[PDB]
Image (tube, rainbow, N blue to C red):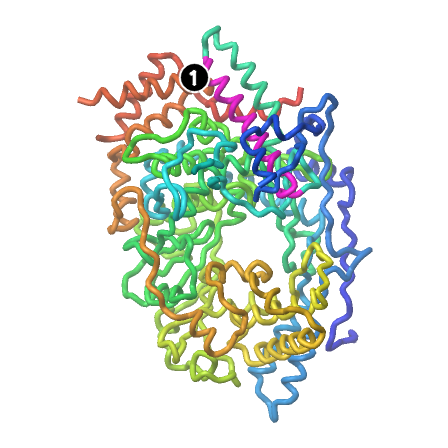
Amino acid sequence: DVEELLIPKVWVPPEDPLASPSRLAKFLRENGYKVLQPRSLPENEEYETDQILPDLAWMRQIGAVLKPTLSLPIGDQEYFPKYYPTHRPSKEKPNAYPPDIALLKQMIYLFLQVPEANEGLKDEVTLLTQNIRDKAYGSGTYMGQANRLVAMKEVATGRNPNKDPLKLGYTFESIAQLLDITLPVGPPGEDDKPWVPLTRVPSRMLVLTGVEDYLPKINLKSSSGLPYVGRTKGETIGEMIAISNQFLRELSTLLKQGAGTKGSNKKKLLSMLSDYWYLSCGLLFPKAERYDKSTWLTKTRNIWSAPSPTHLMISMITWPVMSNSPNNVLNIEGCPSLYKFNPFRGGLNRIVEWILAPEEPKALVYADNIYIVHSNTWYSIDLEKGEANCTRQHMQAAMYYILTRGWSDNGDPMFNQTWATFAMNIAPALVVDSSCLIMNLQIKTYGQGSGNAATFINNHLLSTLVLDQWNLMRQPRPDSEEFKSIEDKLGINFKIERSIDDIRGKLRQLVLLAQPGYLSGGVEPEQSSPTVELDLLGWSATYSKDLGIYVPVLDKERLFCSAAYPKGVENKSLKSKVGIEQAYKVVRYEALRLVGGWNYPLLNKACKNNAGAARRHLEAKGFPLDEFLAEWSELSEFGEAFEGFNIKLTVTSESLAELNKPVPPKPPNVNRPVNTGGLKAVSNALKTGRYRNEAGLSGLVLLATARSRLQDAVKAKAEAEKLHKSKPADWFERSETLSDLLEKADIASKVAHSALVETSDALEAVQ
């Protein structure tokens, strides 16, 4: 037979068959994937900072890491850009991210010390093992990325091709009134201060008084992207700002001229977009996760690393609005959103209480996830490669929404026409159905790019549509022929990831069968306390006897899958305060417990022991552990859930109860009056075809900008303005009304070649 081991041998990854661009080129062409005709980009050249950004010069001598001299894509000579991502591990280097053998051995050890039997304990060893066998953590393979690319093309154009929602009866506004429920939005900013709108360039987002930061913050470690392949966002802060200025300043210039001379500016404008083509192209970053070994060459998740200039600008539209809008099911009646939901602090109990309430059918939404309860069954729905289902217009509808009820006070627009054109006609062309750079090949991107600029909102909209159509055919059961045919109408794919039958029952019985543990007695668990595996944003439910409520345990399969292959540290930082690693381990094992390990006897104890081991080790070695664990959230792969809490990594009986103590939800912030009705109402009321333009002036302003020529943007606001005046209430009528005034002023774009289609072609000039 086959040689079988307790501690499985080192895995030697397969040889990656698409190692070089010559083979990768063949693969895509062979699979009917579009390869673009390679655009070229000016070489980057040294420029004094006290010139291009004169307002942010003193901010060096007193993030803000500035650079005495910037580097801008303005060179005399040109190049074709390359991006060659490292795939850890490989044949040549198989030890990059090893499995947690020490955790396994320890669990096995701790199991053997148990006097007799118990399969429930052994089941932990079995599971943790089966993972180390079946899975491998790493970057995957080009074969894997490329195969995932074709996978997405086959979603977006193959079985059930994507659909323009505007051609399906939906409209900027009808979608916007849907999003009104599923994603409530306030005025931009956070907790100080307010009132700065989209009437100034990125440079001006750092105002002096008596220095305030209004620049949408982003992590200074990720890949910068075009035009600076091989550099980080922190090494290119000033360059990211400078390029954005140049781009926006040049746009206002060409918009503030318009026609004048036979609209010969059209050629100057399609020139400017072709100049800035690199904004439309993002690096194909192979996402490092725990992959199945068998599908090591067939499935690798792709990240679309958007050009930091595109990012800065797209996020300027969304980030200040989305950030200070924490409105969800937890604080608005009828709201189905889970945005900014956090299960600790009382969070999970409330959704579990929401499920238990007799009302049904009901839905819950977060980006590409739809949770539905129907006929007493929990349903976990995802969209097939959410992000590939997105059309260019799906986003411009979302971009509409954010502006109309995020950057508008009571109907009045608070944004330039420059920004209005960028958001409605430019941004979505840069980001959806655009392009990516894998190796030296410039290949098409199908739909939206996974984890690029403003990805959450567009997916959220996509689900909002699925839900809408769900409401229209009288809320069918997710696994019925009817709920499936929703994808045939909308051109959005979705599978049922998981379904729990008799959901209310099983949740109730969690209270009866709760075994003693950290949150049910204040004792180290001898036996695994039962849970309902909701996978609610990756969380499962268990009842704490000590707290008298449901508390979150990280999904069983996610937990062990993580425990098996711990992530890496990327940059070694060579810090070395004797412990770098040892200390990290502490974080590894304590965080594992904290999320959910605390509820799995062996895994808990095993993690505790190994944590204590490293802790005892570093105490003697001298290392200042306490100071290292200050900002631990930033270090662990689970930190995001523990952010804003400033909580010590201890995992005692207290800390789990203090982490889980019910604290009244944060008060809602809604721009317009708060809707207490629900999505069922809005869906039906909207099918009659009669709905009031709740966006006021701004709505019409954007309706014109989209429906007319790119250059005639200032004329489009002027027209719509005159329109708003003439009244003598409904949107379908007002729509045609304004439209006529676009044909009357002869600035309306000719059918099937909208400004969006014009700016998209202009982004791939080649010649």
Q: Check the picture and name the quadrant holding the C terminus.
A: top right
Q: What x and y, as percent, mark residue 564?
A: 64, 68
Residue 481 among magenta residues: no
Tell me the chief SS of the magenta region: helix
Q: Residue tagged by mark 1?
A: 712
Residue 685 found in image quarter: top left
Q: Check the picture and name the quadrant holding the N terminus.
A: bottom right
Camera-nearest residue between 199 and 556: 199
> Residue at the bottom extreme?
115
Residue 235 among magenta residues: yes
Q: Dot 1: what SS?
A: loop
Q: Is residue 453 above or below residue 384?
A: above
Camera-nearest residue between 673 and 324: 324
Q: How many residues crowd around disc 1 within 10 Å: few (fewer than 14), some, or many (20 or more)?
A: many
Q: What x and y, as percent, mark residue 292?
A: 66, 60
> Residue at the front extreme?
210
- What is the magenta range? 232-258
Question: Would you say 398 lies left or right of 46 here?
Answer: left
Q: Residue at x 33, y 20 (%)?
A: 739
